[PDB]
Amino acid sequence: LMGGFGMKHPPPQILIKNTPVPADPPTAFNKDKLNSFITQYSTGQVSVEIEWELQKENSKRWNPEIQYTSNYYKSNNVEFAVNTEGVYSEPRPIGTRYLTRNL
Amino acid sequence: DGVGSSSGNWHCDSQWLGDRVITTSTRTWALPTYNNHLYKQISNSTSGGSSNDNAYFGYSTPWGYFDFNRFHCHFSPRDWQRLINNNWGFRPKRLNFKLFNIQVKEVTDNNGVKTIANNLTSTVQVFTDSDYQLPYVLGSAHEGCLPPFPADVFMIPQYGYLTLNDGSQAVGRSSFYCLEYFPSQMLRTGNNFQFSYEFENVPFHSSYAHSQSLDRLMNPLIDQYLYYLSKTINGQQTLKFSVAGPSNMAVQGRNYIPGPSYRQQRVSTTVTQAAASEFAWPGASSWALNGRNSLMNPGPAMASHKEGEDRFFPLSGSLIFGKQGTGRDNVDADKVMITNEEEIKTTNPVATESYGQVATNHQSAQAQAQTGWVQNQGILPGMVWQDRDVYLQGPIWAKIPHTDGNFHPSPLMGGFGMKHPPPQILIKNTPVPADPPTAFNKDKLNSFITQYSTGQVSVEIEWELQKENSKRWNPEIQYTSNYYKSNNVEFAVNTEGVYSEPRPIGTRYLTRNL
Amino acid sequence: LMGGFGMKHPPPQILIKNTPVPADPPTAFNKDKLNSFITQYSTGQVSVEIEWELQKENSKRWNPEIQYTSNYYKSNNVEFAVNTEGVYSEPRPIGTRYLTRNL
Amino acid sequence: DGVGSSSGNWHCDSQWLGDRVITTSTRTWALPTYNNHLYKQISNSTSGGSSNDNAYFGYSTPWGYFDFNRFHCHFSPRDWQRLINNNWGFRPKRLNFKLFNIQVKEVTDNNGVKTIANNLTSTVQVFTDSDYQLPYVLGSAHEGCLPPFPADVFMIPQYGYLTLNDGSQAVGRSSFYCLEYFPSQMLRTGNNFQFSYEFENVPFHSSYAHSQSLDRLMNPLIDQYLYYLSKTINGQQTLKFSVAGPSNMAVQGRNYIPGPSYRQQRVSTTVTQAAASEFAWPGASSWALNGRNSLMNPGPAMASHKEGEDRFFPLSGSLIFGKQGTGRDNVDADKVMITNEEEIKTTNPVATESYGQVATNHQSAQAQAQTGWVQNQGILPGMVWQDRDVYLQGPIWAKIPHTDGNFHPSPLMGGFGMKHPPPQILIKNTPVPADPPTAFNKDKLNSFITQYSTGQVSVEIEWELQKENSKRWNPEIQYTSNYYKSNNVEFAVNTEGVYSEPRPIGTRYLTRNL
């Protein structure tokens, strides 16, 4: 209902965790679970590649269609770009329904 | 081929095989020049209309089109009688279409007298929208189809289409289609046109009436092993339960329930009834789209009336056909033929009645139990229903709208719903300019020779049959003509040669269990 | 200079003329060229098919490009369509330079 | 490979074959973090500038880039001397580039003291713009190239680009490029990067000076068979004609004429000259684009000065190099090295002189013949010219702008023009986030470990040589060092280890006929 493709078997959840690294344990045995760990965090790169199938348009419409376009008029910043502080912004939501076909 | 050789023969017959019937029909057509070879923008402003529910924008084309989307275009009354009396179902399988014996005529007027002569070198253009790239207008019950009587000569209807509108104005999303932007075959008097079409798989139409009702499927001799709440009070919450059995069938547990409903207002056909108000639009059942109110017509398939109430019909829930010679505007009830769907009363709710009652509160010692009428009920699991019956003069198929989702896309006016129905066949006379000026002028020519075309059209459709295997002992109900003497034979010509269809003929006479 | 493709050997000129059909000549020989002809004109169909080669864009530009688009706002007529009298009109000149590439 | 194994060796040498010379140079580089891993919109508003000729809009990227677009990055002074004294021409053929011995360091500051340690698991990203999808900034004479002295360690310049601007604002046609939207190789300390490039076919650079002038190509002993108008008046239109011969060479017919011109204002290098006004911008020669005035620099290849006028130079028609240690702003003439193109005076017009004189009226008995000076002259048929000479410290190549048309796309600053020049090589340190909070926050991380990277870079270029086959009897002019004693050796290090280039070195010492 929020939009998209419904699947019984969607892309699986990918779960990641840092393995706990205990600190120095006491020299005398204690049966309680360890609660002293080395403070750690992890970093790395993640890549995802998705192949999309396209349905081309075969319209016989004579007049030009409505198309999504940027506005040429001057502005302080370029839409869908970074600001002077390096902050990326999306200025508007973009749908998918601009081309037309008969009902 | 040539001027002096026929490009086709007259084929009009029905062939009845075991599980298949092949219908062939040939008609003579006439095609004039539409819009004087021009495309014209049309709207409710150009037709003078100002109500917002009736507002539109679109275009009228110089092209005509062939329509055979009515059953009587292919089935004779006798063939229809055989089909409905001997088969539990049927569906179209494949199509063959032919245009031949093209004859293009030129008309010249000197002074109050017109002379018609052949123009052997002129052409007629025909193409099929096999890719469904043009608006589909065959899905509406429009006039202009092939006549039911083979001897009648018919005029080809003009092709027009509608697009998105805001009042009488268009929007940027509106589309304009030029039919000359399609490849089309050009035919002189010696040429012919033909193509074949395969119907996509569709369910068999239900040409039967159920011999059982949905609420009477139990064994009338054996109790259920289930209990129902019988009593409640003593005469203290004294809950009492009883076995549901033959003596009380209404409270028995059931696995399936009647189909959806969208209640219609009730109208009596009895004369000398006094109406309390003008209600034909104010009392109408209706759905709204983008601020425009459209009449619910014919709406979901529902029983027209309860048993014994044939005098009542839903305000817009039934197909209304006009008798031969009936006028266009404000005709009496005896000039029209009101169809009814009483055969589906065994599974479908009555059109002019509520679906049922539903609890609306929590009963207690202080509050009495309350119920409310369900005037409209959507699809629920376990529902079963029958689609609207088809008729001899009714539509055959319709194009399923290209949308993300749909439910049971059987056309509400009756017939077979298809994503890829038989393609539109568009035909137009090629313009023949008159004498142009001897000095070049860049403007498009507006002086043309007055022309029209005529010829024969043949369509062959193979239908698959579903034979009946009933074990019913007593004879079935069958459609039959009445032997009693009359001035004219039903489904025949009058003394003036006028063919008439005296009544609508359904398909549901045989019976089968539910 | 008016725009387009310059060619030493462009598409050749296609010339067409109705063959003169003389009227009834005199029964006595006259050496002068005939000047009495049957009034005639001709009509028919003409088809031209042109194959165009395309140069696809491979831009790495992040923000959306400028695109030619029709305006959704309501109007009495659809742009690049016929009027109520069947007159086709082109409401504006359309160039070709909307996509962008580096210099 | 591994942490403890070198990923490449130090290659720095020149190999002289018969018709080819292969130059290899290796340098040590350092790459810091630019813009703190961010992309930033930049403009003349962000740099505080308000003149419209200096207005801009663009972006600064966290990426660095490798530049070796200067001749001294590949040729030692001795190799350059050999090339210019022994060859009539040369051109690049192919390229080999290598990055190896990657070392990524982390910097930690406790209190006024920084500690540097290796981060063996960090990566550096490198990719080449082989498809030329990014703005090309190597076509401008920017600093940051590989040092001429192999022992110098250099800092990688930060990559930035400009797009369309209206004042300090952008327009819809402006483009924003993300360099992370390109596939790039990620290298740890054990990895290396390399690619090969083939130069597109370019003409040989003219490393010669003409031994003849365009106006002295005739036989000095033989008259022409053509006549010229000598006299006109008696002392009546008395037209007199004479043979053009050795005694009057200026009036002889000629088949070819000197190349185009765009006149420069003249500046004297002599001190104690009084200037009449401040003229460095008001007197400048200039071209306008979309309302923005840009200085004509260096403009068309023209002779810097007439014979014996070495004290004069065009206001912006010559390349100006800075001596070692020269400041950035408002330095004296002795702190810069002014190049000159006197070698092309045989075919190209003088930069500070008019191209010639052209008639401006029709002479008659009442009107004296009038002529006008041609300050700018476009290309005419029969014109011949020499392109600007290249220098040891000057640029090598430039990217021809992707446009519909161009004429003689030799870079005006000197070098080889190519539609597909050596691709830009972009390098960046992969950001390494600091410890993130233990509770999820959707904002992008802004706390990173302070890092920089260092390593070696090697570039090998094969050059094709055009040998000289002159029949000249007397010895040629050759570039040579001066034997006379001096405190330091030219093109060597000082007592403080500072390498300096004492003079610009051209390529045009050998001679050939015109």
Image (spheres, coloured by chain):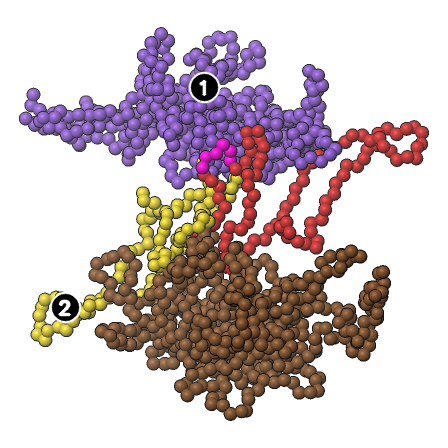
Chain colours: A red, B brown, C yellow, D purple
D62 is within the stretch colored magenta = no
Q: Quadrant of the C terminus of chain D?
A: top left
C36 or C78: nearer the viewer: C78
Q: Residue at x 28, y 25 (%)?
A: D375
Q: Residue at x 55, y 89 (%)?
A: B482
The answer to which image quadrant residue D411 occupies is: top left
Above/below status of A20 relative to B212: above
Which residue is identified by label 2? C36
B385 or D217: nearer the viewer: B385
Q: Residue at x 14, y 68 (%)?
A: C36
Q: Of circles 2 and 1, which is in front?
A: 2
Counting other residues with Cα less than 10 Å from the Cα at mark 1, is it few (<14), some (14-19), or many (20 or more)? Answer: some
Q: Is residue B99 visible?
A: yes
Specify the label residue D321 is tagged with: 1
Name the side, left or right, on which D230 lies relative to D319. left
Residue B210 rendering spot, x and y as whole percentages: 67, 77
Main SS of the magenta segment?
loop
Q: Residue at x 61, y 69 (%)?
A: B352
Above/below status of D271 relative to D450: above
Specify the segment rendered in magenta: A73-78
The chain that hosts pointer 1 is D
**Looking at this rendering, what residue extends furthest in the left direction?**
D236
